[PDB]
Length: 96
Length: 99
Image (cartoon, rainbow over all chains, first blue to last red; front, side, top):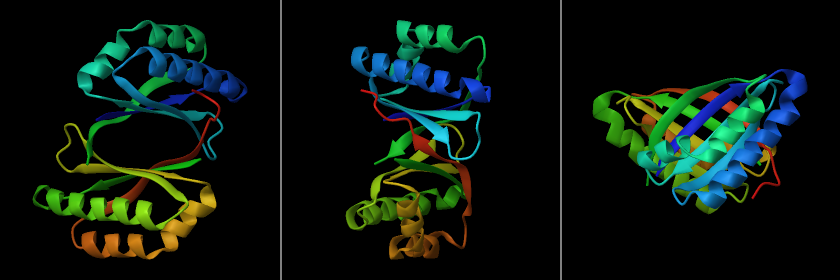
């Protein structure tokens, strides 16, 4: 499996809005993309502005397909006015 | 849930030894620790030396329990001579209720 960790920063008063947008992305991607296997939104325990998306795909091609799909485009429409990112913390493969 | 992302760097000739140690840590923690819910070893797609541990716990207390248990202690005994880390990339809480 192909694991992609993404980091975003948002104004503190936009944190709840970002989290909703992240779950919108997760909901739509998991449901409609056969290559998208897991998609979690994580809030930093102390940094008031920082969130992480922990994404799992069958392979890199599935991630590139996600990048070309409608849900991620809808996600960016929601956050574009205020968010900073994506910053890719890593892309890698699971050691099974 | 409480999510912890850990990063390690190892010399190239110790990458297989690190993976074996990480697989021991993941299987030993998941099998024996009721608060340890998920534990994945991930190798960077290009960086030959870099590994990540993606750990999920019931709450912060369960991570701190993991930290005081015997599985992690043997993991560090296996990797001490060659590894660089842990570097904590993040600790955080999952936003719940999604599909």
